[PDB]
Each structure stands twice: as structure tokens, then as C-alpha cells.
Amino acid sequence: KAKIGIVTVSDRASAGITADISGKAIILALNLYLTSEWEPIYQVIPDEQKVIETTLVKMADIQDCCLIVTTGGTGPAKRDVTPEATEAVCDRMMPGFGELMRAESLKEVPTAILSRQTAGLRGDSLIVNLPGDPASISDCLLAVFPAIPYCIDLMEGPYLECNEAMIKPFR
Amino acid sequence: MVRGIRGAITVNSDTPTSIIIATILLLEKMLEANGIQSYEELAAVIFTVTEDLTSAFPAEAARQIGMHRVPLLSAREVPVPGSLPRVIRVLALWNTDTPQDRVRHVYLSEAVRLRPDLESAQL
């Protein structure tokens, strides 16, 4: 039974004012893609840097889910601290995730260079950032997910089985 | 006694996933905004993609949320030059006595530009 963490970062959704929506899209894309048994671990937290550090650490080590996904807090507003919380909790940085997603939301929206997304590894767990817009969540998830099952396999994580119709993994 | 519910949403690429996710997101938001408890209240639901969205059906997404009960139908909204591209639009027909000014319309993503202005021209 593989496990995946989905984390929504927004004071609006954490206080219950608005529906998360952005995280719902991540779960929907993951109900696609994946043909294998998988369980989602999912919390909605505010733009508190230490609170983000905890939910990531708790999911990466105690829950031990192989892949963690964040959404929001990646822009240039002083509120946004989602990337900074990822750099503290990870031993190593995967710079190719942010560079690719920044260019593949860019040929559609030019105000995507204003992103601070990044990704890293907490030992055996892979954490990746996504923005708040769901329409660019599918565009960003689609762009990096082919390498993720191979990456999780490289860290001896659970084998991710992919759907040939919805996505295309490389190994 | 029926009311219409307009919906709209955009995608950032023409892939089967992005079409299905955007469709379900818009569909489930349209029902939640109006308090739709069950699909039995809907008479039928209708979708419009543009000319540039083709890789998948809005029905295939609607069937993965249990709307086999619901009659579905889709086509291509007019390919107008300079119009908002890659937009999926929804007209769900709702057996209800709700007043017309009460029905929540749901324009999401970059498709909020299509949100009807309350005072636009009005010749």
C-alpha cells in the first residue's frame, strides 16, 4: 500500500472560508495517472513556515509517504513561505523540477517566472511544490510526473504503476 | 419548472487529464454553489469545448463522478477570433423553483473574464 501526501497552503482554506479546490485537483490527477493501490494523506494548513515544516516532516517520516505535494505560497507576496519550508526539511535539492515547471507554465502564462517553486528529498521521500491555480496544477503535474515513479524506485520506494492512457512514465 | 446554470473554466494544455480534472472541478463546484444534493434534480447537462480542445470528452469525466444517471451532451462553442481559448462551458438544467436571480453561476480559472458584467453596454 503506497502513500502520497497532499498539502494545501492557504490561510483562506485553512480557516474554512473557501473550498481548497487546488488540493482536490491534485487528488483527482492522482486518481488518474496511478493504476496501483494508493492512499492519500491530505491536510490543509496556513501560510506558517514552521507549520509547513511540520506537516512535511510528519508526512515524510512518520507517515512515510513517498511523494508529498504542496500548493500555494510559491509567489512573490511576503506571505508566501512554502519554498523556504521545503529547503530546511530536505537534505538535497532537485533543481530540475522547478526549472521545468517554470518554463511549461510560461509558454501559457508569462507571469509564471514570478514563481519560487522548488523540490527536494527528505531522505527517502520526494517533496514537490505546485502553485495555487488548478489549471496550471495539471500542467505542472503532467510535466514532472513521468520521472516520479522512476525517482521513487531509485530511492527504493514503492513501485508506482502508471496509466498509459492518462500519462507516460519513463524508466 | 426548470432553471439553467452556466459554467466556465479554462485549461492550460489539451490533454485528457487536464480536460477531465477541469470538468469535474467545475461540475462539482456548480452543484455545491447551488446546494444540489443529488443528481436526480438535474434533467440533463450540456457541455461546450472550443475548437482547440479535442483529446477527451467532458462526458467521460462526468461518468467518473457517478453521473451515468444524468443525460449528457457536448459540442463545440463557436470558434470566434480572439475569444478566450481552451475554455469548457457548462449548461446544466435543474428541476427547481429557485428564482432566476438566485442561481449561482460558476466561472473559474481564466474563464472568469467571461463572467457577465452586471452593467455592460445595455443598449
Image: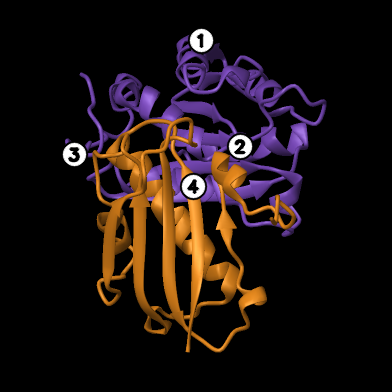
Chain colours: A purple, B orange
- First of labels 1, 3 by sequence position: 1
- First of labels 3, 2 by sequence position: 2
Q: What element does badge 1 sit on?
A: helix
Are the residues flagged by discs 1 and 3 from a single subunit? yes
Residue A66 lies, in percent from the top left, at 41, 34
Residue at the disc numbered 1: A95
Residue A153 lies, in percent from the top left, at 29, 24
Q: Nearer the viewer, residue B76 or A111?
A: B76
Q: What element does badge 2 sit on?
A: loop
Q: Is residue B109 left or right of residue A167?
A: right
Q: CA distance from mark 1 to mark 3?
A: 28 Å
Q: Is residue A151 left or right of residue A133?
A: left
Q: CA distance from mark 4 to mark 1?
A: 31 Å
Are the residues flagged by discs 3 and 4 from a single subunit? no
Q: Pinpoint the chain carrying mark 4.
A: B
Kind of residue indicated by mark 4? Ile
Q: Residue at x 27, y 49 (%)?
A: A37
Q: What element does badge 3 sit on?
A: loop
Q: Nearer the viewer, mark 1 or mark 3?
A: 3
| Image quadrant occupied by the C terminus of chain A | top left
